[PDB]
Amino acid sequence: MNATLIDCCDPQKPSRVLFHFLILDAPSPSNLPTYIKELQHRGVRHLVRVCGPTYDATLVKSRGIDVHSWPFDDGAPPTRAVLDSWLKLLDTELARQQEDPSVPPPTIGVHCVAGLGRAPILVALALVEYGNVSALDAIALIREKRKGAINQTQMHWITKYKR
């Protein structure tokens, strides 16, 4: 498994990880049980799919992983609805940790198909919003681990973003 781990760190204490992001490939229906096991084995709390369904999410939900189906168009930046839902989820996970010192940093998975566009740009945005990393540095960081990630339109949108 074919996954890229990107840490989003506390701006104040860059020692401290806020979230672990996993950029993943989409599962095939036939390999779905193995795939779920591999998510569980990496402590995945939340799975976000930003592509059109290619499988039955209920099988994942039943194994303790929250699944979020927020499709947006290939080559596109997140819609405002997806973005707000993403920040809402991350805000909630952030409050969960602050409220309870017994909660370690959550791993949050994100897949589409290629992992070159839609998945990475959500992660990039999290780095900008919570890690306080500049847009250009978030892109470079993702590209280190995933060559060819993020098209020109996605690049422009993340360079322009504020809450």
Image: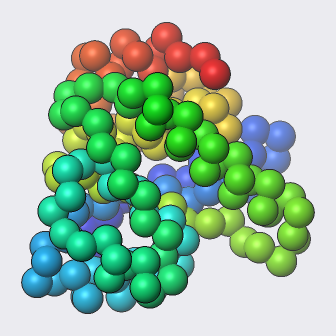
Observer able to see residue 127: no
| Residue at (16% x, 83% y) in the render | 31
Q: Residue 134: where, in percent of width, then height?
A: 57, 23
| Residue at (30% x, 44% y) in the render | 71
| Residue at (20% x, 28% y) in the render | 75
Identify the image quadrant of the C terminus.
top right
Identify the image quadrant of the N terminus.
bottom left
Q: Is residue 55 left or right of residue 135?
A: left
- Whether 128 is drawn above or below 115: the answer is above
Q: Residue 50: where, in percent of width, then height?
A: 31, 47
Q: Residue 120: where, in percent of width, then height?
A: 36, 42
What colour scheme does the image use? rainbow
Number of numbered labels in the structure image: 0
- Whether 46 is drawn above or below 91: the answer is below
Q: Quadrant of residue 61?
A: bottom left
Q: Is residue 12 left or right of residue 105?
A: right
Q: Is residue 49 left or right of residue 31?
A: right
Q: Quadrant of residue 82?
A: top left
Observer able to see residue 73: yes
Q: Residue 157: where, in percent of width, then height?
A: 40, 16
- Whether 150 is drawn above or below 9: the answer is above
- Whether 60 is drawn above or below 96: the answer is below
